[PDB]
Amino acid sequence: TIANKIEEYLGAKSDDSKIDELLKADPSEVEYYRSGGDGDYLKNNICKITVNHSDSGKYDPCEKKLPPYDDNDQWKCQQNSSDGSGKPENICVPPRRERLCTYNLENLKFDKIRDNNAFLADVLLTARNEGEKIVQNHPDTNSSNVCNALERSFADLADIIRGTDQWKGTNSNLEKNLKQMFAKIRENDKVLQDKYPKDQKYTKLREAWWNANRQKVWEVITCGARSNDLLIKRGWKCGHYEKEVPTKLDYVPQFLRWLTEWIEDFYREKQNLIDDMERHREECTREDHKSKEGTSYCSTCKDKCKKYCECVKKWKTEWENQENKYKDLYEQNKNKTSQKNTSRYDDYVKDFFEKLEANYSSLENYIKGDPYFAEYATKLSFILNPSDGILQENCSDNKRGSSSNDSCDNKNQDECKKWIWKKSSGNEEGLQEEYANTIGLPPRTQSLYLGNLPKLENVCEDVKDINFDTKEKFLAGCLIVSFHEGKNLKKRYPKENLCKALEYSFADYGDLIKGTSIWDNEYTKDLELNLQNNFGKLFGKYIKKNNTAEQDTSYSSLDELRESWWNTNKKYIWTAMKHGAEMNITTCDDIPTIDLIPQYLRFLQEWVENFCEQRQAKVKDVITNCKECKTKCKDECEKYKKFIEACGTAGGGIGTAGSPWSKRWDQIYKRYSKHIEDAKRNRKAGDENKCVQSDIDSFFKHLIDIGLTTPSSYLSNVLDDNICGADKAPWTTYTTYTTTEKTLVVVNVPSPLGNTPYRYKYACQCKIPTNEETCDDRKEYMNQWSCGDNYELCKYNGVDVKPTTVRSKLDGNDVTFFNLFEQWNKEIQYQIEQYMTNACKEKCKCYKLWIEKINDQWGKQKDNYNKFRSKQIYVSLSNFLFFSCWEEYIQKYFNSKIKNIGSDTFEFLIKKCGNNSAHGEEIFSEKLKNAEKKCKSCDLNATNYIRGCQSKTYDGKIFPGKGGEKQWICKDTIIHGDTNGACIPPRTQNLCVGELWDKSYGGRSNIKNDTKELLKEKIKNAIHKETELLYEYHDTGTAIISKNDKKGQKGKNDPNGLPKGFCHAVQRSFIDYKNMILGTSVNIYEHIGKLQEDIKKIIEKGTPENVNAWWKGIEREMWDAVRCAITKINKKNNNSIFNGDECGVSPPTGNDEDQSVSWFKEWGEQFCIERLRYEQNIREACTICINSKSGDKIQGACKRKCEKYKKYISEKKQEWDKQKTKYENKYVGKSASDLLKENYPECISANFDFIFNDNIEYKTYYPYGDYSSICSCEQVKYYKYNNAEKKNNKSLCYEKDNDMTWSKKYIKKLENGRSLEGVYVPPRRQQLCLYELFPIIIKNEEGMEKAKEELLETLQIVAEREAYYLWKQYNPTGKGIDDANKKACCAIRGSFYDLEDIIKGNDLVHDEYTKYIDSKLNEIFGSSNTNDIDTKRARTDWWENETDRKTIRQLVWDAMQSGVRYAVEEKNENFPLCMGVEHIGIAKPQFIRWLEEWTNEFCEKYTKYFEDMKSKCIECKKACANYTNWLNPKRIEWNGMSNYYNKIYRKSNKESEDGKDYSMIMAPTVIDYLNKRCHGEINGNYICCSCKNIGALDLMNEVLNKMDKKYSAHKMKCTEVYLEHVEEQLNEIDNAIKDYKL
């Protein structure tokens, strides 16, 4: 076995060993041993394996906590354990092996490996730990030293796993272990059960397994090696990407390997001695020995001389003895004895013994070739032939604050051609294997006079040898290289670009002398070796930080004492290059601070300057001849076309190297994005003075928090914004377009690098554009349906008509019509709403423009629906539209199309839909018309005396009068406001009817002998008096609405000079009189019913209804009357005389004229003001529970105030309940809490449905609602899993609903014109359990830096209980424990991510809870003045830093785990196969997560409903009805969501709609994203959707408009049964309408 020829046949047992396909184990299976294992987190990159893969307690990093590789000159050569008795050293053992990081394999005693895969994972973990301990600990030359040491440890591991160990130690403990696991493996496989030769076939089968997994183990063990290591001396890199085990060292004999090891270790250390005896060589005695001065400076020379002598003597003895031990077996190889016999194997030791001992005295060419042997001499005889300029600072990059030019200055210090992109460089100019073809080495770099050098010391042809001994000589070599290169470059180019390219070349040197060259060539990776071993001699003596304290003063790690050397002395390099290319004079001390930028980024900026210069040259002519296009500029546009479209043809740009610009940009984007993602997950960031320190990772992490993902954005930031293009096309605006492939309609999105420059797309081939497309590209309104005598079908989109026959009955294309119409009719209706809410004038023109589109579409649909009915005449678009608009409601709340007990919603529907009971389609025409009309005196003695009205008292008598208050009269009464709905306001009750009514003994209508005129005049006078009284009542602050906080009830004054809320009071009083005049739901005074009767009589006698018209006419009269009132009052007022422009020039609008609605609004404002007053009083009385006895309840002051609040809220509970249910019934869809919140900003902190909570626990555990917080002084503490007491009933939110649907509501209105929509809240997220947060948050408003404690506690509590309840909702609601556990784990992870986004404030919902929660988080973390982005950063990293060794999003995850454990224990099951991971990754953007969840649940429901319907089909009416009722509303979901995706994909934190950082999503379309996302299993982590043969994933969009094949088989039956159901349900609805009409 020469190890070169015999082995290739003795090897090759990994291809003809079909067991290998099952013996090729691999990690990346389901969670490993429930100890943090994972599948994808390793298949993506096997390198990033952690200890948490088998048990991490037994399998921790090797627990031999004996100093590794940093020890004395220990060499087990003497009597140590058994070697030394008769055989002094059985085998040449270095300390390296004794530190072989296999103590992970001492504590492996366990059996459930259940695959070769887990055992592979264990051994690979050991290999990776060994590789790390090697690389971080190897103070040496050190390139060859570290590389050889790594491969030698790999070969030692090979022997160990193969069992061919020769060192004796604690191996049997793991030896019989690996025996038993291998036995387990061979009993797992039937094919390998063909191999049971005793003993368990250790040797042969372990060799087979080693040859099966050697590739993986070698690949991983070298992963922890920096790229600038040059591992393998075959491509002499990092040796990691060799794609095959490059070394054969694992195959050489173990004992031969170790004797070579040992001789080379002696060799390295003896060269160390021969050079370090020259430390004080100025006084080292190369002459007569002197020791008279008595110091350790001259006698040391002889000391080390004799030490080296004794070393060589002892090594001589041990060498010759080792020779004998491998030789004294001559006449006994082989007998079967174990006295002094060494037995190694049957294939590799035999040839060794017969060659090197029997017939040959010494060994052969191999060990002579690579490992040198006679540096001093060979003294072993198994091989013969013995030959016997600075020293200064580093920098940590203080970075600036985004001044649009991206130049980080400097930081702390220290004391002492043609852009070939081809592929990873094989044997010529290319890129390193990391950057196979991603950024594309520019042509100036190649041929830079240094990469054109095999060796630096070959500075010039004139010099023959090396002067590099002193620092100055090496620095001068660098200087002359720099000067010559500058000369060459100036020779090249001619100017201003000169300095730019000179800066780039300077950065190239600055990276080469730091060894991080992204590229490489035939003269690279060897000059790099020369640089390293040169630095080893001079400036190589300070590398002594492979230690435990590191002293932070020697800066010792080859790079640091190399890159630090570069940071210094680069002033001299740059000046010399300036003194090279003669552009020297102070033009461009000054240093080009660009070298700190990663070389990849500048290889981007270069080649972007190239593309820009070419493009601006090619467009400058274009922008001329297209001037509106004048006559003929299509030719030069076509030149630009072909330039930017060429697949590297002759006609086209240069630098693209073949593939067109689009593909190359895509590669660049992928590389940059994955760099961003790698930078996201790493624990290194900006430290000395709050600055990002170091190499690519930290710099990229600095870009994040500035955005600057999507290299387009980077470019837009760092470019000059004018280098390319007369058309200032920004690097945002991806500008979609399509082209042919160079199968014909392929599309692309290059941002300012698509054909047809920025605006001149229309202008090419002049065709002066019309108004429609100028709207279309703006994407203003986008009705994408394209209707253009059969049916003239209104096609939706690029989903072509596929008419199918399953069948005057319905037949073929016929059905499609209805269904298409069914969707169009639906969607357009829905569509109309948003654009109704929509409305410079450009969008107005767009709005008109799509209006006639819709009008014509409706015209054609109406036309051909008549044709449809005509075919089916042997159901009229007035029946059907009515039915469908009713169906919207009946499916929204009900599902259930039978129970019709509304009796109040009926009015709302008939106003909306069904006047005259399904007679007319006019709802649609009316909506269209509405879309059309949306194209955007008493200053006399006004003694208005009343004998029966005095100062207002309903809110208490005016000061100093105390008491006399009124309350809210309620369900139907007589004395005040006979009204079945909302309760009666006290202000209404004390209305001051004036002289309009009197008593005269008690009770009397005095308006009996009057007519219109004097009655109205008396009304006017009464209004005057009552508004004067109201104004006085509000000036004094007696009015509850008028009272402010602790201030004198007048601190808030409106910007009109009027008492607070007195505006609203006057408006409500006017509304009260208005609704009183005509018969409405008001009787608001003793017997006003007779007053409406009196009006009806006294008016409807002379006019001949007419009361209504007369009131409408005199409405302006009475409103100008109250205007004149306010004028005279404010001129009587001590302030300035205001005008009739008191709030409302016209009377209050008829919209907010529903007396119930106005009453409710007034009540809500009253309630908010009183709640705030009570809260103020509480915080006054609950800030010093003071002196509480257990349990520590409120002690009477806090207790009394808070109990007053409790009683108040107790009665307002039923009050608000009744009022809100009446309102919501009357105003279906809208919510009372909103109405209050926008109409009254006074209560934003108020949270109805919580202060008025209905759950009993949320009353008994919450005795004071929201104020069951700080009112209750108990200092709630979170309890972990183990705690004897639990969080039982602490936050017992009810069990989650299962079938509540997605909502577009509560989506935040984002900013100026951003306005995200088409995004809908996932069900589980909107029914999120977060209630316990709200109360203490109210307490948390005060007491910063102490509230965060409570926040952490409540987050843990709520996370735990939420996980418990969500698991309960998923898992025990089912028995398929595998997939149920997977789905529950996915839901829990999604919930955790949503909660984290809430903490980070990146959540998109702003419902009553989350809105206030986010506001309070901002006010808490943002102390007083921090910018919004800074507040986000603070509440983000506070979420990211630990309290005690564990970060917030680790404690929360633990709370989730403990909640799941409670759920499992209660259900009495096993812990899930998921949920056990102790380290989850980072979250995709919440929109992406919601999209994934939506697809998952949609495919689930589809596979359920369609299967049910197919199985069913007389009765399957219910089945396909369920299917189609779930489908259609779910269809508009997808359209809006896909539209939003297309708006936001590949955009980064400064160009996406939201500020949220996207662009980890590289997919042109959402369909392409999903089919490339979860086309597989549904495992607990990172694959959470799973869709299967939905049409037997573009059939996703195909089926939403139910047109695909898989449904066409049943479409005909389903449409007929649907139509019959429509007929019967229409009958029912008209019957119900007729029923209500009485």
Image (spheres, rainbow, N blue to C red):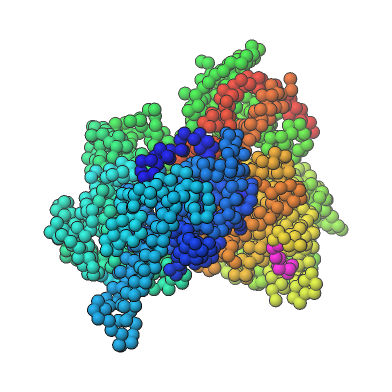
The answer to whether residue 1124 shows anywhere in this view is: no
Q: In this view, does 405 lie above or below 1074?
A: below
Q: Which residue lies furthest to the right in this view?
A: 1001
As drawn, the residue found furthest toward the left would be 462
Of the 4 image quadrants, the one containing the N terminus is top left
Q: Is residue 352 magenta?
A: no
Rendering coords of residue 1063 (x, y %): 63, 59
Which residue appears at 51% of the width and 15% of the height? 789
In percent of the image, x 84 and y 55: which residue is there? 1003
| Quarter where residue 1244 is shown | bottom right
Q: How many labels does the image show?
A: 0
User: Residue 186's image quarter?
Assistant: top right
Q: Where in the figure is residue 1235, as x and y percent of width and height?
A: 65, 51
Residue 1444 visible here: yes
* Placement of the C terminus among the 4 image quadrants: top right
As displayed, is residue 1425 above or below residue 1627?
below
Q: Is residue 568 left or right of residue 1285?
A: left
- Comparing 483 with 1435, the one in front is 483
Answer above or below: position of 1620 versus 998: above
Give percent across and percent down for residue 382: 35, 55
Name the one closer to the observer, 121 or 313: 313
Which residue lies at the image location 49% right of the left edge and 24% below the top edge? 800
Magenta span contains residue 1273: yes
Q: Is the magenta stretch mostly helix, strand or loop?
A: loop
Horizontal and vertical percent position of residue 1252: 74, 55
Residue at the extreme bottom of the image, as rendered: 293
Magenta part of the chain: 1270-1279
Q: In this view, does 1300 lie to the left or right of 171?
A: right
Residue in the image at 25% along x and 81% along y: 288
Q: Is residue 830 left or right of residue 947?
A: left
- Considering depth in this image, is 605 or 685 the residue closer to the camera? 685
